[PDB]
Image: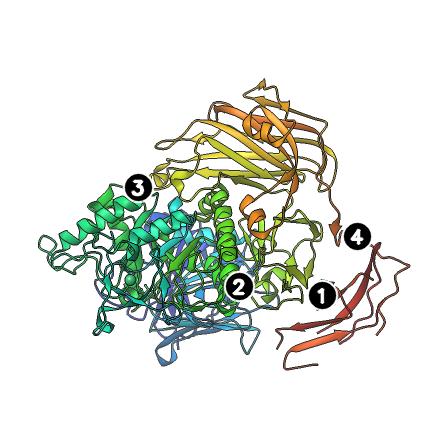
C-alpha cells in the first residue's frame, strides 16, 4: 500500500504529498471548491490520462488546469497541526490524518465535513479503490446512462462500456457520480470501474477503476444545479441542440433493399399507396424473387418505396418531422452510382427535397468518416466533409460498429465529427450528434440514445423513464430513444403511451425497418394516429418552453429533472417512489403510464403518482382538475387518450402555433399559457435555431412575470413582459402577443400598458371575434389547450381562460404590462382539506418476498395510508399493497369535511 504521509509541501503549482512508501501525489487547487488529487507511482504526473489508442486526442476535460488560474492555489495554506496536515482557503479545509493518510473535506460556508475516507487508497489486483463514509440520508446519482436506474444508494453500478441496451445494462457510461452530501467526483481515467454505494455495508461507499494510479476531480457545492455546473466547467457545457433536433426524426435505409408483391397477411407485408402489399428483402435474402429496388429519390419506377415517399407520408398524416437519416442500415449507402461523388450528388438531391419540405438530413455512420485518400475516394467510402458541404447534411448518428470499443474511441470520434460540421459550414451549422458508448465530456458534442430494445411491451416504457432521469443527473440533458423500439410492435396501447410521454423529452427517433411493423406515428389505426399527432403537435406548441429549458440545461439543471432536483427537501423525491416520474423543466410533472393495468371501463390504473409539497396545488394539464401535494396518489383512472401531466400552479409556459418543423413557427407571434399563483417568473430563450453563433452572444432573452393572488383566490393580476435583450441573424423585432390566463370567472376589468402608454382593450362578444381582432380580451369557457387532443379523445376538454391579444410591437424597444382586477382561478382542490374531522371514525382494524398488503374496516369516500412516513392517498376501498422493499402502516379515513385522526403505528 501507500503508508503514512511524512509531508505536504507547497511546490510552485500544486501541493506535493510524500508517503512513507516514497510514493507521491499532487493536489492542484483549481478554484475555492474544486481540487485534483493524483497519486502517480510513475512520478510523471502528466496532465491527461493515457487513452485506449494514441490517436485518441479528445480529452475528458474541456478546461486545462492552467485555464482555472493560480489564485485559489495562492489563497490555500498548508499547516502541520500534530496529527493532521491541513490545506485551507475560503472554500475548503482538506484534512489528512498523518498515520492513516485518510482525507476528509470540510465545506467552510456550511461548516460540515462533506467527504471522509474510512480506509486508505488500495491498489490491489491492478485496481485503484477509494473507500468513503456513507451517511444514513446520503443519496447518490450519476454513472451515465444506467439502464433502468437513477438513485444508487444501497446499489453497485458498472462504469463499463457494456453494449447492453436493456434494463440493468449501461448504454453510455460516465466516471462521474455525486452525493446529496454536496460533492461530485470525476475519475480522470479512460479505464472501466465499479461504484458500490453500500450495497452490503451501508456505511461504506467504494469506487474502483482498473489501473495503477488514482486521479480524480472533487468539487463541493450546496445545490444540484451547482454540482452539474462544476462538472460542465470541467468536462464541457452540453451542446444546445438546434430547434429541429427536438422534433421526431425518421431513420431507415432507402438505398439497399427490394420490395416484393405478396398477399395481404403475409408476415412482414406492408400496404403501400398503390393498394398492394409488399415484403422487404435484403439483396442477399431475395433468391429467385422478383422485387423493386428502393432508392432515396424514387427516380427508378420505385417512388412509393423511397425516402421522399416517407417525408410525403409524414406530410400527408400532418405529423411533425424535424430530420431524416436515409442510410441507417448495414452496407446501405446513400447512392447507387459507380462513385462517392455520384453518391453525394444523389444524397444532395434527397437533401434539397427534404429541405423544400422543412426537414433536415442526417447520416448514420458504421465507420470512419474520411476516405483513405480524400482527394481520390472509392465507391462505398465515407466523406463527411463532402456529405456536409456538398450534400447539406446537418446531423450524425454513431452506430455501435463505429464507437463500440468505448471510452476514448467515442469522444475522439464525436469531437472529430462535431469539429467537421462547424469548420465545413464556417459555424452556419451547430453539431447535432446522437451517440452512445460515451464517457466524461461526451455531452459537449453529442446527446445519447439508449440503443436497441423490443417495443410493443410495457417494459420498453417502464425501464426507459429512470434511464432518462439518470442520464440527465449524469450531466447529459440531450437524451432520447427509439419510438416504440427498433424491434417488436403490434401493441397499439404501448405505441400510444410511448408517443404520449416522449412529448416531454428531448429526442424521438422513429428507427424503422427492423420491427414487427413500420416505425412511424401512423403505423396503427386512426385512433392511435390521431393521439400520436395530438401529442406531437403539443411538443411543437411547447417549443418556446422546450428551447428555454434546453438553454438552462447548457449550464444548469437538465430538461428531464429527477423530482429531487425541484423538491430537494422531500425524502420521497430521492428514492424509487420517484423512479417513474419527473419534472419536464420547472413547470410540468410527467407521470407516464408504464403498465397494462386497467379497470373494467378500460382506463389504465396509475399507482404511485407522487405530488410533492403539502402547500402546492397541482393542475391536470388537460382537464384543469386541482390536486393538493404532500401525497402519492394510487388508482388514478387514465384513459387511452390521456397521460398524467400536472402543471405547477404559478407556471408561465411560452407557447407557439402548432407546427411540423421549425420553419413553420410564426416568429412574429408570442404566446404565454399562465396559471397565476403569487409572484412567478420565466426566462424565454431564443436564437437562430441552427448556427454556433449562440456561443458568441447571438441570442435574446425575454423575462415574463406573473404577480397574482394565491391558488383559487380573488385579487389583482399584473402580467409583465420585459423588453427583449440581445440579437441574432433574422431576429424579428415586431411581434403580436397572446396571453392565455386560466381563470374560473369573467374579470371585473382588463387594461394594458405598452412601453409606458395605455392600449385600449375591447371585450370580445365571442371566440370568432376574439380570434379575428387584436387589442382585445375574452373570457373563454371553451378554451382547449390542445384542439387535436379534444378531437382525438372525443372529449371537449374545455377549460375557462381569460385570453388577452395585443397588436404587433417592438419587443426590444417596448415592454408589456397587462392588469386584471377581480382575477380568480378557482376549482375544488382534491385533498385540499387535511384538517381532522372529529365526526369521522378512526379506521377499524398475501405477504410475499417484498409486497406487504394492509386491510381495515369501512367508515369515508377514501382512506390514506402512511408508509414509513409517506402518505399514499386516493385509496378508494379498504385494502392497499406496498412493494419494492428488501415498515410502518398508520392509516386514516377521508370524508367530505377532512380526514380522521391517524390510527396507531402497525408493523
Ligand atoms: C446500438 C446500435 O448501434 N443500434 C443500431 C440501430 O440504431 C440501427 O442504426 C441499426 C442499422 O439500421 O444498427 C444498429 O446497430
Ligand atoms: Ca430499406
Q: Residue at the far right: name it.
A: 839
Q: Residues within 10 Å of mark 2 (few under 14, many from 20)?
A: some
Q: Residues within 10 Å of mark 1 (few under 14, many from 20)?
A: few
Q: Which mark is residue 356?
A: 3
Mark 2 residue element: helix
What is the quadrant of residue 665 in the picture? top left
Q: Quadrant of the N terminus?
A: bottom left
How far, Cα to Cα, is label 4 from label 2? 36 Å
Q: Are marks 3 and 2 in contact (CB under 8 Å)?
A: no
Mark 3 residue element: helix
Q: Nearer the viewer, mark 1 or mark 3?
A: 3
Mark 1 CB in 8 Å range of ligand 1?
no
| Left or right: where 305 falls relative to 835 | left
Give the mark nearest the N terminus, 1 or 3.
3
Q: Residue at x 41, y 54 (%)?
A: 29
Q: Name the residue beneath numbered marker 4.
A: 833
**Count of marks, rendered view:** 4
- Residue 503 visible? The answer is no
- Residue 170 visible? The answer is yes
Q: Are marks 1 and 4 in contact (CB under 8 Å)?
A: no
What is the quadrant of residue 629 in the picture? bottom right
Q: Name the residue beneath numbered marker 1.
A: 869
Q: Name the residue beneath numbered marker 2.
A: 493
Give the mark nearest the N terminus, 3 or 2.
3
How far, Cα to Cα, is label 3 from label 2? 34 Å
Q: Nearer the viewer, residue 856 or 2?
A: 856
How far, Cα to Cα, is label 4 from label 3? 57 Å
Q: Position of residue 95 (x, y in %)?
A: 50, 62
Amino acid at each position: 500500500s501507500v503508508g503514512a504521509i511524512v509531508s505536504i509541501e507547497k511546490a510552485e503549482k500544486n501541493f506535493v504529498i510524500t508517503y512513507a512508501s516514497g510514493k507521491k501525489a499532487q493536489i492542484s487547487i483549481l478554484n475555492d471548491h474544486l481540487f485534483r488529487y493524483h497519486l502517480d507511482p510513475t512520478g510523471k504526473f502528466e496532465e491527461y490520462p493515457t487513452p485506449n489508442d494514441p490517436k485518441h486526442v479528445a480529452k475528458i476535460t474541456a478546461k486545462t488546469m492552467a485555464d482555472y488560474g493560480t489564485q485559489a492555489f495562492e489563497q490555500t495554506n498548508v499547516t502541520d497541526s500534530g496529527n493532521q496536515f491541513i490545506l485551507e482557503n475560503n472554500g475548503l479545509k482538506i484534512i489528512f490524518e498523518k498515520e492513516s493518510a485518510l482525507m476528509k473535506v470540510l465545506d467552510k460556508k456550511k461548516n460540515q465535513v462533506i467527504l471522509e475516507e474510512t480506509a486508505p487508497l488500495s491498489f490491489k489486483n491492478d485496481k485503484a479503490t477509494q473507500t468513503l463514509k456513507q451517511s444514513s440520508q446520503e443519496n447518490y446519482f450519476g454513472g451515465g446512462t444506467q439502464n433502468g436506474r437513477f438513485t444508487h444508494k444501497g446499489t453497485a453500478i458498472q462504469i463499463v462500456n457494456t453494449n447492453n441496451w436493456v434494463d440493468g445494462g449501461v448504454a453510455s457510461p460516465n466516471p462521474f457520480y455525486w452525493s446529496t452530501a454536496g460533492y461530485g467526483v470525476v475519475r480522470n481515467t479512460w479505464k472501466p470501474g465499479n461504484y458500490d454505494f453500500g450495497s452490503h455495508d451501508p456505511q461504506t461507499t467504494t469506487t474502483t477503476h482498473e489501473g495503477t494510479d488514482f486521479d480524480a476531480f472533487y468539487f463541493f457545492n450546496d445545490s444540484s444545479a451547482g454540482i452539474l455546473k462544476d462538472y460542465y466547467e470541467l468536462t464541457g457545457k452540453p451542446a444546445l441542440m438546434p430547434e429541429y433536433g427536438f422534433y421526431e426524426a425518421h431513420l431507415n435505409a432507402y438505398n439497399r433493399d427490394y420490395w416484393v408483391k405478396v398477399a395481404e397477411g403475409t408476415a412482414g407485408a406492408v400496404k403501400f399507396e398503390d393498394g398492394n402489399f409488399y415484403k422487404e428483402y435484403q439483396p442477399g435474402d431475395l433468391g429467385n424473387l422478383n422485387g423493386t429496388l428502393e432508392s432515396l429519390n424514387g427516380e427508378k419506377e420505385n417512388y412509393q418505396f423511397s425516402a421522399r415517399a416517407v417525408i410525403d407520408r409524414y406530410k400527408k398524416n400532418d405529423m411533425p418531422l424535424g430530420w431524416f437519416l436515409p442510410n441507417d442500415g448495414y452496407g446501405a449507402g446513400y447512392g447507387q452510382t459507380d462513385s462517392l461523388d455520384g453518391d453525394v450528388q444523389n444524397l444532395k438531391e434527397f437533401t434539397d427535397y427534404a429541405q423544400a419540405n422543412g426537414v433536415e438530413v442526417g447520416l448514420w455512420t458504421q465507420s470512419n468518416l474520411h476516405p483513405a485518400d480524400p482527394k481520390n475516394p472509392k465507391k462505398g467510402e465515407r466523406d463527411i466533409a463532402k456529405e456536409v458541404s456538398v450534400a447539406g447534411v446537418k446531423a450524425l448518428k454513431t452506430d455501435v460498429a463505429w464507437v463500440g470499443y468505448g471510452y476514448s474511441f467515442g469522444l475522439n470520434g464525436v469531437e472529430d465529427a462535431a469539429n467537421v460540421f462547424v469548420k465545413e459550414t464556417d459555424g452556419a451549422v451547430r453539431p447535432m450528434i446522437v451517440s452512445l458508448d460515451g464517457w466524461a465530456g461526451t455531452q459537449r458534442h453529442a446527446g445519447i440514445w439508449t440503443g436497441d430494445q423490443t417495443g410493443g411491451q410495457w417494459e420498453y416504457i417502464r425501464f426507459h423513464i429512470p434511464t432518462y432521469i439518470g442520464t440527465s443527473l449524469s450531466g447529459q440533458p440531450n437524451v432520447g430513444s427509439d419510438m416504440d423500439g427498433i424491434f417488436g410492435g403490434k401493441n397499439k396501447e404501448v405505441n400510444i403511451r410511448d408517443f404520449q410521454w416522449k412529448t416531454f423529452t428531448p429526442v424521438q427517433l422513429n428507427m424503422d425497418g427492423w420491427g414487427s411493423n413500420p416505425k412511424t406515428p401512423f403505423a396503427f389505426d386512426q385512433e392511435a394516429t390521431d393521439l400520436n399527432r395530438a401529442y406531437l403537435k403539443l411538443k411543437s406548441m411547447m417549443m418556446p418552453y422546450n428551447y428555454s429549458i434546453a438553454k438552462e440545461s447548457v449550464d444548469g439543471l437538465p430538461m428531464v429533472r429527477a423530482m429531487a432536483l425541484e423538491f430537494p427537501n422531500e425524502g420521497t423525491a430521492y428514492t424509487k417512489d420517484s423512479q417513474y416520474q419527473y419534472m419536464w423543466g420547472p413547470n410540468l410533472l410527467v407521470a407516464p403510464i408504464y403498465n397494462g393495468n386497467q379497470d373494467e371501463a378500460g382506463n389504465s390504473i396509475r399507482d404511485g403518482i407522487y405530488l410533492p409539497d403539502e402547500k402546492q396545488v397541482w393542475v391536470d394539464l388537460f382537464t384543469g382538475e386541482k390536486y393538493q401535494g404532500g401525497r402519492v396518489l394510487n388508482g388514478v383512472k387514465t384513459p387511452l387518450w390521456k397521460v398524467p401531466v400536472f402543471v405547477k400552479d404559478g407556471s408561465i409556459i411560452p407557447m407557439t402555433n402548432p407546427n411540423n418543423n421549425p420553419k413553420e413557427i410564426q416568429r412574429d407571434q408570442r404566446s404565454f399559457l399562465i396559471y397565476p399563483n403569487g409572484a412567478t417568473s420565466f426566462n424565454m430563450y431564443e436564437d437562430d435555431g441552427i448556427s454556433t453563433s449562440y456561443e458568441a452572444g447571438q441570442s435574446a432573452t425575454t423575462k415574463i412575470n406573473s404577480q397574482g393572488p394565491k391558488s383559487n383566490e380573488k385579487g389583482d393580476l399584473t402580467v409583465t413582459i420585459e423588453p427583449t435583450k440581445g440579437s441574432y441573424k433574422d431576429f424579428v423585432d415586431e411581434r403580436s402577443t397572446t396571453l392565455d390566463l386560466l381563470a374560473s370567472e369573467a374579470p371585473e376589468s382588463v387594461t394594458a400598458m405598452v412601453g409606458g402608454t395605455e392600449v385600449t382593450l375591447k371585450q370580445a362578444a365571442n371566440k370568432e371575434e376574439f380570434l379575428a381582432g387584436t387589442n382585445l380580451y375574452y373570457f373563454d369557457k371553451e378554451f382547449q389547450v390542445n384542439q387535436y387532443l379534444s378531437e382525438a379523445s372525443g372529449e371537449k376538454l374545455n377549460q375557462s381562460a381569460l385570453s388577452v391579444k395585443l397588436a404587433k410591437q417592438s419587443v426590444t424597444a417596448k415592454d408589456v404590462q397587462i392588469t386584471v382586477k377581480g382575477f380568480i382561478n378557482k376549482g375544488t382542490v382534491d385533498g385540499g382539506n387535511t384538517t381532522v374531522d372529529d365526526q369521522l371514525t378512526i379506521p377499524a382494524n398475501k405477504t410475499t418476498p417484498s409486497s406487504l398488503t394492509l386491510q381495515w374496516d369501512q367508515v369515508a369516500t377514501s382512506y390514506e395510508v402512511e408508509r414509513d412516513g409517506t402518505v399514499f392517498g386516493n385509496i378508494q376501498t379498504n385494502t392497499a399493497t406496498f412493494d419494492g422493499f428488501s415498515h410502518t402502516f398508520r392509516v386514516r379515513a377521508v370524508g367530505k369535511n377532512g380526514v380522521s385522526e391517524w390510527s396507531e403505528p402497525i408493523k
